[PDB]
View 1 (cartoon, chains in turn blue, red):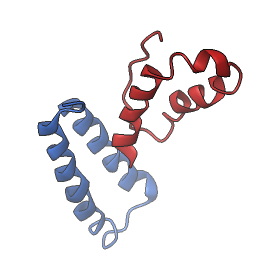
View 2 (cartoon, chains in turn green, purple):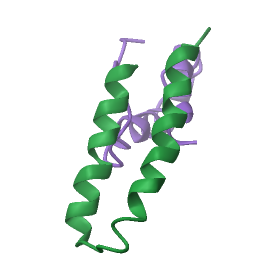
View 3 (cartoon, helix red, strand yellow):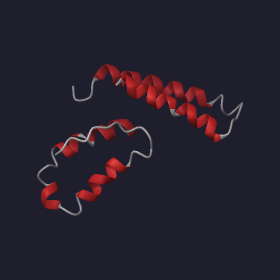
View 4 (cartoon, chains in turn green, blue):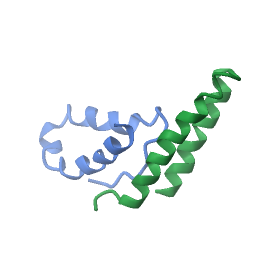
Length: 50
Length: 50
């Protein structure tokens, strides 16, 4: 396989699990900088798994 | 092509993509011979964003 399969399934976990995190930063609505620095952490976390 | 290894995550990592779009417009003769692997390091970019 060109790009490993097992890891590409993990990307779907992060893809939709992060969408759920937004609906809490709309009720508790924090400034962009806060909601961004968490959505940036899931990028690093996921790219390690690769 | 001299291997350029990196993973696209930050929106600011467009520099490594724009580096080919610029190289392919100065030396179309030289880009026509290593279009092969310059492709697969860019095929990695397409799995991540789209």
